[PDB]
Image 1 (cartoon, each protein chain N blue to C red):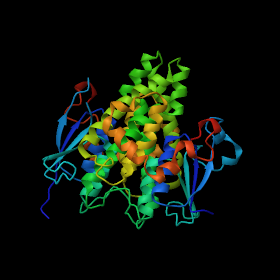
Image 2 (image 1 turned 90 degrees about the horizontal axis):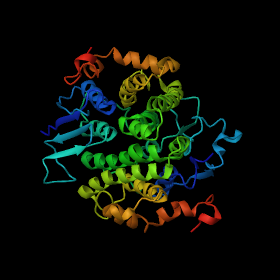
Image 3 (image 1 turned 90 degrees about the vertical axis):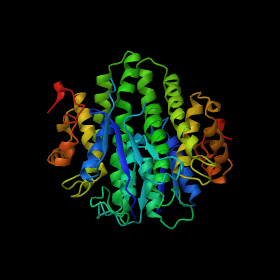
Image 4 (image 1 turned 60 degrees about the vertical axis):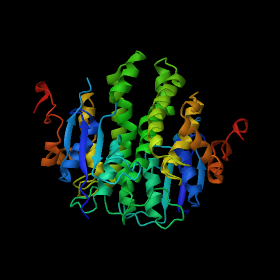
Length: 217
Length: 229
């Protein structure tokens, strides 16, 4: 097998969904072409080429506009990669726990606290910051109860999984609306352990090419 | 103890996904209806079933729980995780709902469709967010209709690339299982399904399936008499 997928990521330094993929690519040492897209229509968007597109066979590339599907694609399309981000298939219970945590974040927090929805909330004369902070706080409470069951060094045991990959950019996004991370001690410990990772530092929202100077670290 | 217990509600779209998947795969389960309109998920009987109190809740029993080994059960409060769990925990089931592992591109396409519904539509148009919108003095029905119309436009674009008889090719996948209750939820808020011709056709093809009829929101033990059909 001589199959070598080519990856290009249309992303944004501050997008929490783009940050999942940045983290996942660095942890797995998978080279990608970064195409920054300044949001101030889908971001992120991962374009995979040099593959068999079994959906659109005459097409050179295959697009994935949803970060969770893009993450699972990385797990499935690269079976020889030295770092799986899921427990193995023979452990469906641990995989379900990992996916539960990803879904609380990807389904219960991110979609109700993004720019699009904050704007809809301001259109109803609400306070988008308060709306987002209360929803993030509630979602992190559910994350924390699941981490009480599974966390070791990381969200699920002592290895990094997709759960930690989702957790990190969601902490960045939650802190921006003033959520107090200290309310969720296992989440906080796992977050900090993840920031010790060089791959997480390379994926950092303050450390990308399109990070504005005011925001750089 | 049953292998599977679904605490569901007849008109919950996430519960609908699970009912459809169980019928499609002929997997026996025990149904406990929890009336979300009466706030029954806060009652004492459902106390010890944490999460906090989510509907649907899938309780899985008689298993080796490799996360909490002192227990022979676990519960899953996220329908997407629960759907994937059925695929992996029952690998020899007569109806797999994802294309095989040797076609990761088609599994990615299926997951993308599920994610649009499960991430971009259902969370912003569910009962919790509608109540929040109502408290702002907005119209929750209009809010949800706009958001579902927008999500369906993105689904329809993906179906243009993949759909045959069903969402992805000619076989039922998890994309179809997510689509059906999403169409039910969207129509409930006045979305015009005819604007999305591929979605409409796939939805009508799914409604030909007896399993979908057994999972139908109008055909559950807890469907009120005036909503039955």
